[PDB]
Image (cartoon, rainbow, N blue to C red; front, top):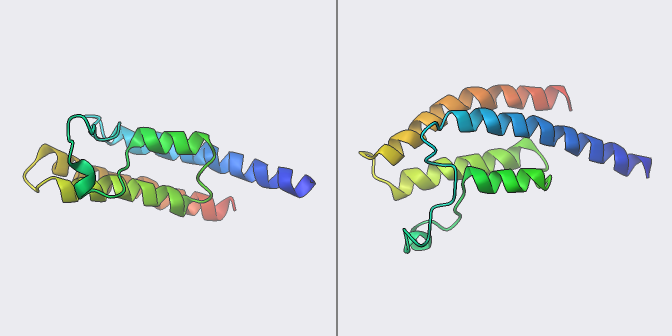
Length: 121
């Protein structure tokens, strides 16, 4: 139908906006602490601690499958990256500290993305 196509065009354009959002958020992690999944070879007990692992590569796979239906779903995954790190790692660690900086700096980017999504429908 013509409606299913129009909807698909909306999803494509959302995917295009979320791709730029993801690139901006990831620049706020220059150390690449959050780039890839925590290795279960190197942290074999991780899943005993963290029930819903997340990272930027896993978000990118979902994004390219147009697996994000709205910005809320995308923010949920970003928030998991931060919140998982801040639980697993102690406050006095480079990992925790990197999450805090990503959270603070990403908030700016996400604040305007929410407006661009409401604005452009």
